[PDB]
Image (spheres, grey):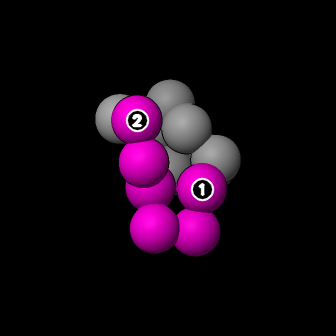
Amino acid sequence: XCELCCNPACAXC
């Protein structure tokens, strides 16, 4: 994903 979360804009990380 991003680092921990797999969002397009990276949220909750």
How many numbered circles are shown? 2
State the residue at coordinates (46%, 68%): 9
Q: What stretch is highlighted in magenta?
A: 7-12
Few, some or many C-alpha atoms within 10 Å of disc 2 (few <14, some 14-19, many ≥20)? few
Q: What kind of residue is marked 1?
A: Asn
| Residue that protrudes farthest toward the bottom in the picture | 8
Marks 2 and 1 in Cβ contact (< 8 Å): yes
Q: Residue at x 55, y 38 (%)?
A: 5
Magenta region includes residue 8: yes
What residue is shown with label 2? 12
Residue neighbourhood size for the residue with mark 1, other residues' Cα within 10 Å, grouped as few (<14), some (14–19), many (≥20): few
Q: In this view, does 9 lie above or below 13?
A: below
C-alpha gap between disc 2 and disc 1: 9 Å
Residue 7, image x, y percentages: 60, 56
Q: Which quarter of the picture shows residue 3? A: top left
Q: Quadrant of the C terminus?
A: top left
Question: Would you say residue 9 sits in the magenta stretch?
Answer: yes
Most prominent secondary structure in the magenta stretch?
loop
Mark nearer the N terminus (2 vs 1): 1
SS for dot 1: loop
Q: Which residue is drawn at 42% across and 48% down?
A: 11
> Where's residue 6, x and y in %?
64, 47
Q: What element carries label 2?
A: loop
Residue picked out by circle 1? 7
